[PDB]
């Protein structure tokens, strides 16, 4: 008799088509199970259907959920309180918006264990909970507001909230998606060691497949609502059966990072000792603080090649992306292209003759490409600020670029609303190479995409170079998707270069600490 | 919080120094000569110190040292205001105990039970109460209650206890009761679907606790801010409300000064109401900063 | 939870702001008269019907009605300590009848011998005092008249023959701001503020020294200056007012059930007129008399006094009121006060044959007494009948509507009226139409009429003094200085907490008789 | 591509918008062409017919002086609609331009304009209007329009600045400046179409409030002169017959209430369409 | 006097 025996299920959202269409899973009352699935596949909705937190339109229309014999598919709002906190726990996804921003975190943790009445012994246990969940200084960190903690501490506190009543089953609804890998490993290694001595079961809901196989014990794969394959973990990665699992394991960067990666003097970009110095007026208006976002970086970028810049948040890799494009003023550096960038050329005459040979590609597809346009008027724009002939030229070109980024060529009146981001990024790529530049600056252009959509954009940029002879400056936040494309790696920490060498002297023999833990932090 | 008020008052200072300029400008610059637009008062007052700046300086010094001017009844404005403030204060306590009790008690229900007949009805009634102007609503209420179904007095008239000051209060509060019922409803209905609410209800504690410590605590801040900022329209409505009910408050004094065309005693009262409004704006911002820690540390 | 500090024993009455300081010989309006008559006490007192009785004087004797001898009751006092004697009367009259001081009630001292050489030009004949007022001893004094006047003893109770304290003849500019009388009431010396709050209110308290004919039965009055009679009536119904003098015309068809045995209605000695100065464009000479005989024949008085006043007015039949003795409603030549558009359009043409017309015709009134209805009705009637454009012009206060008229600073037609002082017809005609009267606002000058009235003011008996007034009105019917409209029917109303309200012959309540508690 | 087409289609099936648009069209036609409905002079007063019941010769009756209320309530609509529209048409331009400038060009403009709108927000609309129309001895329509516009802008400017500086965060203006476009052409082409939303949503409500405040100003005696017919000044003289028992009061008041309610509910619908998100704190 |  398992501790969770869901079989048959359907969750319709307001007389629309169903989101879940027949899922069936079971937790063996002490084991670890993963609910691997692509985005929008109804993998998290399922969780929200087990607890009862179906948002504002949901309703179970088939099957039944049975937690340890007693059926609970009937959400008896009064009976659910004997099960909601003390027998089934829930760890949310977003760390910033899952805490009331007007209550100290200590109050929110001491109100989550309060079944017995006391004021002093409960504020002396909501601190021990935060101390055992793992937290630098649980004395004063429990006296701050949810907006003064930093990313990983909010999640380390959400875990303590979730494990307050000693549940028999935890539901970790994608707990470490929005965290950088360095703490995305520590938080998971601590959770899987905390729920290992309490006997608690665990139900990961991830979007990776090589992560679950490292953590979980039984993996279940979901597509569009239906379970596709489910078996032992260490036999679902090395011997898949369903074609979906095949194209899901052959598109993970954790395999292909061990490939052959088949491939005029060069040295176009030459950076030397860039520096940016930010001052903040926090507190008194005359006690300004000193902070270096970018501190003495220097490199040289050879033509017809690639160079990836990595580093977690607060590494100034996004500020360095602006100082190169000319969208931000440096302090003590030069980024001279050949004779460009303020020395002889980019003074008043090459302020436009430079924009037509260096163009950026931004991070999320939904911000760029303003709503009140069409796919045509968005690609035609960089030909309208410069000058090219009208309908003969300006129409023939746009419907030829569309064919290079492999778009149906019938999406020329669609506003960016009905575009299903992932092919909305193929429009930001086509707009970039409209004037045939020779440098692209991909500022995490592919970080915010699905697992299968991301594998195609990297495979599209890699052959959009072998023909045009482009020259990329890729900017990522993890060593995972590099081995495929990049030929040279630069690592940054706290805004200062750490190691710089080829992508083989870094993926097989690194000579630094902080870049040797970025290797042992990928799900491999 | 300590370094927030030091920036709030420093921002208030130019607003005061600039709002006094507009009043003195509308006093001094007019089509030809305000001395004829507003005789021994032309040499003693306005001693013809043509360097406008120093005249403004002396004017501000007089305003500071308790000297406001002279009312149309021969008494200094200080005396008439100190004699007529208690009545308008007791009138403004009503219409603020109405718009904050009934308004909030209806908005909370219409938000928690949104999409229903009650919600539709309260929204369509709030949208109607704003349409009706203040003066016609006041006179209709006065007729229907005082004259026809004799319950309330027709006019208060210098005997103003909370007993017979209850109909003018309701009339003055029904306007802006249709705002504190359409704002709190839209706040609650959108705050009851947040993420921290789901995380708080997914850890045991019962429904009353959720509603009172996670929804209302977070959604009652804009309501308080709007109640603080509504004083500017409450002042304007008090004039028309104390005109037809014959109440001897600041509104009634200003109504008489407007009716009898006594121009030197309207500016002397409005230059006090403006300062009071600025003070209450600052004192409401100092509470909005204490109820939300994201601006306190911002 | 709150309220007021005044005792529930003061009798609240309505009133209005005096346009002039509180000096007896300087006021010519009822808004100030209804307070001066409370404050002071003259040689004779008028009861409700209007018959004079000896108030301060001990005897007023004569032998041939040209030589008068007046004595004074010993033992009177102003509310300051200083006695009342013959000097307080003689000096006050001499100050009132001086040309330099420019008083409004100066002409009233015309019958007295030695008036020409005291009032008039300040050159070629200069004596500061009249030669008719002589003081025999501290108490009695003698008075000489030019010609034997019939109604001299009757007018001695007027508010212009009041005594003034000695300390008034040293600074008459502060007296008008704080009078010190000797009558039934006195200005309540306010420890918590002033007694008189301009444009707000004024309250009086009884005078413990008064032993006369009008001893007050209440315990103080408070006149409240209202901004409109609608609010006045709402306050009367709500219990915030004790006596409402004039019911607004918008409540004349409901008052019978609203008040319900707390009202009364009867004739009064008041009238209403429409005036236009003789100093306007197109309104002087002959065109300007035709242009007034035209305005007089284009107003439907019977329709106005029926559709607006619910029947509580009387269309005018002459230049006086209807409740006065000797009044005649059938004078020859009266058929110039009738509605006739076919004639109103002949006179306008007879005037345009002298000078064409161009401009607007504005009728100015004070909005704090309920004149908008009949003023707009008159304006629409004139417009419809003549073709010209006439409009109404409201002003917020009587005290501020009269100060524009008094110093000739108005440039449009205006409403006006007259509330009688003593029941005599000549009193409705002389102060408005003599040569240099104080209340002669239009600018009328007719020596023929002046002499025809001065020959009526000397008739032997009393019935032969009315025929001559009716003959003198035959000149006003031919000149038409002002346009008379109607005569009043005064309606007053009191509340429950008052028990002895009664009205006089001229529509004012009988203060000093109102018993409240 | 004509964005507003899909918004039209989305709000075209909403009865709250449909009835509002119908009422607004009717009000605008009554205000534009009065002589199509009436045939008599508003100012002609025949005193021989003073208080008549509504009959076949007067659809609304006849007030004390003799006028018929139909024409007096049509031409009042003309005047009130004119005054209300002429002021919001200028408040829109001025406040929107100032809020767009201060809110897209950063500081050294934002500081000055924020201090100015803070100064102008410290004094209400009715109080300032009364004070300034007091010493305005010669008053007419354009003066009331100017005095209403002088004090009605700050809220519109605040909303416009808030809506523009939020747009400046989304990085399509960044992609526009990354290919060469001086900040003014960026301002126009991208920031104006994507930020002229809530500004209209609040301009409609401001128009309604302007109508209301002009009516209540003309009721207090200081407003439109007596030479023009208007609700307020008509209500002010019709309110005195109610005690005697004549419901003349309700035709001008009813017309005014319908006119204001139309614009109020139209503004609510337009808010629901163009910007339903900022409905949790402004209101 | 003159009526009010
Ligand atoms: C509120 C209900 C009525 C209250 C009664 C009056 C209060 C006392 C008045 C004072 O005295």
Image: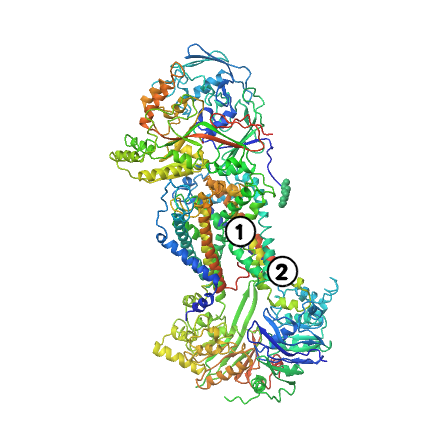
**Nearer to me, A91 or E1:** E1
Q: Quadrant of ligand 1?
A: top right
Query: How many dots with numbers?
Result: 2
Give the CA distance from mark 1 to mark 2.
Answer: 26 Å
Residue C86 appears in the rendering: yes
Residue D113 appears in the rendering: no
Q: Describe the colour scheme in one phrase.
A: rainbow
Residue A116 figure quarter? bottom right
* Residue indicated by mark 2: B217
Mark number displayed over residue B175: 1
Report the chain holding disc 2. B
Q: Does residue A329 lie above or below D123 as drawn?
A: below
Q: Residue C346: image x %, image y %? A: 27, 34
Q: Does residue C447 lie above or below A47 as drawn?
A: above
User: Which quadrant does the N terminus of chain C fall into?
Assistant: top right
Contact flag, marks 1 and 2 (Cβ < 8 Å): no
Q: Residue C486: image x %, image y %? A: 40, 31
Report the chain holding disc 1. B
Dots 1 and 2 on the same chain: yes
User: Which quadrant does the C terminus of chain C fall into?
Assistant: top right
In this picture, residue A389 sits left or right of residue C232:
left
Secondary structure of residue under mark 2: helix
Which residue lies at the image location 53% right of the left edge and 46% below the top edge?
B141
Of the two numbered discs 1 and 2 on the same chain, state the one appearing first in sequence: 1
What crowding class fits label 1: few (fewer than 14 Cα within 10 Å), some (14-19), or many (20 or more)?
many
Residue C328 figure quarter? top left
Mark number displayed over residue A114: none
The outermost residue toward the top is C63
Q: Does residue A506 lie above or below D2 as drawn?
A: below
- Front: mark 1 or 2: 1
Q: Residue A188: image x %, image y %? A: 65, 77
């Amino acid at each position: 008799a398992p501790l969770l025996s869901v079989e048959g299920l359907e969750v319709t959202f307001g007389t629309d088509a169903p989101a879940v269409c027949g899922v069936d899973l079971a937790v063996r009352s002490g084991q670890t199970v993963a609910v691997v699935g692509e985005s929008g596949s109804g993998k998290s909705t399922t969780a929200a259907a087990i607890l009862g937190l179906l948002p504002a339109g949901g309703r179970i229309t088939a099957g039944r959920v049975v937690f340890d014999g007693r059926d609970i598919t009937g959400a008896d709002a009064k009976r659910l309180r004997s099960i909601r906190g003390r027998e089934i726990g829930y760890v949310p996804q977003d760390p910033m918006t899952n805490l009331n921003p007007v209550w100290k975190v200590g109050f929110q943790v001491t109100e989550a264990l309060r079944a017995n009445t006391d004021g002093r012994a409960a504020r002396r246990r909501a601190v021990e909970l935060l101390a055992e969940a793992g937290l630098p200084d649980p004395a004063k960190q429990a006296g701050r507001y949810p907006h003064q903690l930093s990313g990983g501490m909010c999640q380390r506190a959400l875990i303590a909230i979730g494990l307050a009543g000693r549940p028999r089953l935890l539901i970790a609804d994608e707990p470490t998606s929005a965290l950088d890998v360095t703490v995305q490993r520590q938080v998971l290694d601590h959770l899987q060691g905390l729920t290992d001595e309490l006997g608690t079961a665990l139900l990961l809901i991830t979007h990776d497949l090589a992560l679950a196989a490292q953590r979980a014990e039984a993996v279940v794969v979901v597509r569009r609502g239906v379970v596709v394959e489910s078996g032992a973990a260490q036999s679902i990665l090395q011997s898949p059966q369903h074609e979906y699992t095949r194209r899901l394991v052959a598109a993970a960067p954790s395999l292909t990072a061990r490939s052959r990666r088949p491939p005029q003097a060069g040295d176009i970009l030459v950076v030397s000792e860039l520096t940016k110095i930010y001052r903040e007026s926090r507190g008194a208006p005359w006690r300004r603080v000193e902070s270096r976002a970018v501190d003495g970086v220097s490199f040289r970028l050879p033509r017809a090649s690639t160079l990836a810049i990595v580093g977690e948040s607060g590494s100034g890799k996004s500020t360095l992306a602006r100082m190169v494009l000319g969208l931000l003023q440096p302090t003590s550096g030069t980024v001279v292209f050949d004779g460009t960038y303020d020395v002889g050329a980019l003074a008043r005459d090459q302020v436009l003759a430079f924009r037509r040979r260096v163009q950026p590609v931004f991070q999320n597809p939904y911000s760029s490409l303003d709503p009140m346009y069409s796919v045509f008027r968005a690609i035609e724009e960089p030909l309208r600020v410069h000058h090219v002939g009208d309908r003969r030229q300006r129409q023939r070109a746009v419907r030829e670029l569309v064919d290079q980024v492999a778009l149906p060529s019938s999406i020329l009146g669609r506003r960016p609303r009905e575009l299903s981001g992932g092919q909305r990024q193929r429009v930001a790529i086509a707009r970039a190479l409209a004037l045939r530049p020779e440098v692209l600056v991909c500022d995490e252009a592919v970080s915010a995409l699905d697992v299968l959509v991301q594998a195609q954009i990297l495979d599209l940029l890699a052959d959009l170079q072998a023909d045009l002879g482009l020259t990329y400056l890729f900017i990522s936040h993890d060593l995972a998707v590099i081995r495929q494309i990049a030929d040279d790696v630069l690592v940054m920490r706290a805004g200062r270069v750490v190691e710089h060498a080829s992508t083989e002297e870094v993926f097989s023999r690194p000579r630094h600490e902080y870049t040797r833990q970025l290797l042992q932090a990928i799900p491999g | 919080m300590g370094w927030y008020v030091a920036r709030r008052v420093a921002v208030m200072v130019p607003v005061f120094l600039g709002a006094t300029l507009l009043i003195y400008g509308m006093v001094f610059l007019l089509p030809g000569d305000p001395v004829a637009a507003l005789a021994a008062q032309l040499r003693s007052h306005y001693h013809l110190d043509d360097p406008f700046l120093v005249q403004y300086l002396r004017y501000l010094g007089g305003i500071l040292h308790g000297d406001l001017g002279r009312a149309y009844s021969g008494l200094p404005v200080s005396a008439v205001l100190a004699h007529a403030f208690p009545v308008t204060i007791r009138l403004a306590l009503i219409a603020l105990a109405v718009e904050a009790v009934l308004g909030i008690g209806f908005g909370v229900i219409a938000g928690l039970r949104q999409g229903g007949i009650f919600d539709s009805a309260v929204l369509v009634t709030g949208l109607v109460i704003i349409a009706i102007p203040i003066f016609v609503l006041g006179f209709l209420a006065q007729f229907l209650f005082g004259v026809q179904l004799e319950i309330a007095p027709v006019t208060v008239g210098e005997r103003a206890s909370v007993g017979r000051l209850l109909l003018p209060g309701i009339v003055l509060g029904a306007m802006s009761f249709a705002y504190v019922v359409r704002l709190t409803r839209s706040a609650v209905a959108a705050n009851a679907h947040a993420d921290y609410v789901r995380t708080a209800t997914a850890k045991g504690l019962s429904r009353p606790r959720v509603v009172t410590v996670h929804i209302l605590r977070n959604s009652l801040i804009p309501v308080v801010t709007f109640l603080g900022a509504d004083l500017g329209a409450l002042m304007g409505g008090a004039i028309v409300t104390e005109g037809i009910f014959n109440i001897h408050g600041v509104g009634g004094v200003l109504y008489q000064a407007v009716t009898r065309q006594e121009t030197p005693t309207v500016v002397s009262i409005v230059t006090v109401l403006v300062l009071i409004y600025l003070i209450t704006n600052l004192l409401v911002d100092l509470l909005y900063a204490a109820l939300d820690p994201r601006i306190r540390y911002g | 939870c709150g309220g007021g500090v005044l005792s529930p024993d003061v009798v609240l009455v309505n009133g209005g702001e005096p346009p002039n300081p509180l000096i007896p010989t300087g006021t010519n309006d009822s808004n100030g008269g209804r307070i001066i008559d409370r404050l002071f006490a003259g040689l004779m007192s008028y009861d409700a019907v209007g018959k004079p009785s000896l108030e301060v004087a001990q005897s007023i004797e004569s032998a041939d009605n040209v030589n008068y001898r007046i004595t004074v009751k010993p033992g009177w006092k102003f509310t300051d300590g200083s006695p009342v004697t013959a000097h307080s009367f003689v000096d006050a009259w001499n100050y009132g009848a001086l040309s330099t001081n420019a008083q409004l009630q100066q002409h009233f001292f015309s019958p007295i011998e030695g008036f020409d050489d005291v009032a008039g030009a300040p050159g070629d004949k200069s004596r500061t005092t009249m030669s008719g007022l002589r003081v025999v001893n501290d108490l009695e004094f003698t008075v000489r008249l030019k010609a034997p006047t019939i109604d001299f003893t009757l007018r001695l109770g007027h508010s212009s023959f009041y005594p003034l304290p000695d300390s008034a003849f040293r600074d008459m500019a502060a007296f008008g701001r704080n009078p010190i009388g000797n009558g039934p009431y006195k200005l309540a010396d306010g420890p918590a503020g002033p007694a008189w709050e301009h444009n707000v209110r004024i309250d009086l308290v009884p005078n413990p020294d008064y032993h006369g004919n009008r001893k007050p039965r209440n315990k103080g009055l408070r006149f409240e200056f209202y901004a409109n009679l609608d609010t006045a009536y709402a306050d009367l119904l709500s219990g915030n007012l004790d006596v409402l003098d004039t019911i607004p015309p918008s409540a004349l068809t409901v008052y019978q059930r609203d008040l319900g045995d707390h009202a009364t209605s009867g004739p009064a000695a008041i009238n209403q007129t429409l005036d236009t100065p003789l100093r306007l464009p197109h309104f002087g000479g002959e065109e300007g008399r035709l242009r007034r005989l035209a305005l007089s024949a284009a107003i439907n008085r019977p329709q106005i006094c029926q559709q607006i006043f619910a029947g509580t007015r009387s269309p005018a039949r002459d230049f006086t009121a209807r409740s006065l003795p000797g009044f005649d409603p059938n004078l020859p030549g009266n058929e110039v006060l009738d509605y006739d558009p076919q004639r109103a359009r002949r006179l306008w043409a007879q005037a345009d044959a002298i000078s064409p017309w161009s401009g607007r015709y504005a009728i100015a009134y004070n909005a704090d007494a309920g004149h908008r209805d009949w003023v707009d009705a008159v304006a629409n009637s004139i417009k419809n009948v003549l073709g010209i454009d006439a409009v109404a012009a409201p002003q917020p206060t009587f005290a501020g509507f009269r100060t524009q008229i008094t110093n000739r600073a108005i440039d449009s037609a205006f409403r006006a009226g007259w509330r009688g002082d003593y029941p005599s017809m000549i009193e409705f005609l002389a102060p408005l139409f003599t040569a240099g009267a104080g209340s002669n606002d239009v600018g009328y000058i007719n020596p023929e009429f002046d002499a025809a009235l001065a020959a009526a003011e000397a008739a032997p008996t009393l019935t032969e003094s009315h025929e001559l007034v009716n003959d003198a009105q035959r000149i006003l019917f031919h000149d038409m200085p002002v346009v008379p409209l109607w005569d009043y029917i005064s309606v007053v109303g009191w509340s429950s907490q008052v028990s002895n309200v009664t009205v006089t012959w001229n529509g004012l309540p009988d203060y000093e008789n109102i018993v409240k508690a | 591509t004509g964005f507003w087409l899909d918004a039209w289609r989305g709000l075209r099936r909403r009865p709250k918008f449909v009835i509002a648009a119908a009422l607004i069209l009717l009000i605008l036609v009554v205000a534009a062409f009065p002589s199509l409905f009436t045939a008599a002079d508003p100012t002609y007063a025949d005193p021989s017919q003073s208080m008549l019941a509504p009959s076949a010769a007067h659809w609304f009756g006849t007030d004390l002086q003799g006028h018929d209320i139909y024409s007096r309530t049509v031409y009042g609509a003309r005047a009130s609609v004119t005054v209300g529209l002429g002021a919001t048409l200028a408040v829109f331009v001025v406040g929107g331009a100032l809020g767009a400038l201060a809110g897209f060009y950063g500081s050294w403009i934002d500081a000055v304009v924020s201090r100015v709108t803070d100064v102008f927000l410290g004094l209400p609309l009715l109080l300032a209007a009364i004070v300034l129309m007091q010493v305005m001895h010669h008053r007419t329509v354009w003066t009331v329009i100017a005095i209403l516009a002088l004090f009605g802008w700050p809220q519109v400017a605040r909303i416009a600045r808030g809506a523009v500086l939020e747009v400046r965060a989304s990085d399509y203006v960044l992609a526009a400046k990354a290919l060469g476009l001086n900040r003014f052409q960026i301002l126009l082409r991208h920031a104006l179409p994507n930020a002229v939303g809530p500004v209209i949503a609040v301009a409609t409500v401001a128009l309604g409030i302007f109508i209301v405040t002009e009516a209540t100003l003309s009721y207090l005696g200081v407003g439109l002169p007596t030479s023009v017919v208007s609700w307020g000044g008509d209500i002010n003289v019709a309110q005195t017959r109610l005690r005697s028992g004549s419901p003349i009061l309700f035709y001008p008041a009813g017309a005014l209430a319908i006119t204001v309610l139309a614009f109020m509910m139209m503004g609510d619908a337009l808010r629901d369409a163009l910007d339903p998100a900022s409905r949790a704190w402004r209101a | 006097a003159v009526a009010a």
